[PDB]
Image (tube, rainbow over all chains, first blue to last red; front, top):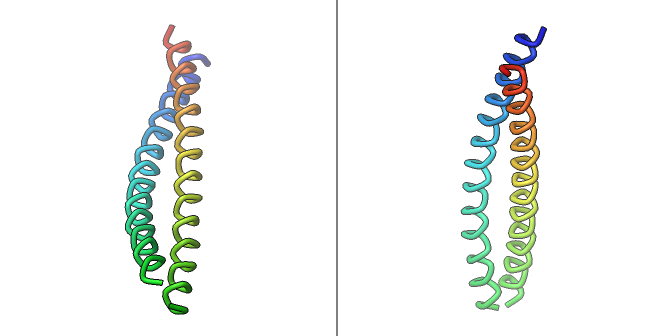
Length: 48
Length: 48
């Protein structure tokens, strides 16, 4: 029973750690596209 | 001047959306990290 509880817990932990890395990579890409967009607006607000 | 203000207003909307998506991505990241920590403790406790 405990040997099954061990294996299941670790597999989940690994699956979560893989999901985190993917979400962190996406977030970084979204943070870059934002700073690019933000700057274009600071330029556009200045042309006004 | 009118067209610039519209595009300035546009980017401010996009700017804020991308920040809000960033904050959501970080909160998701934290929740997954907390789950990943609990699963590892279950992992270790089972091996012992």
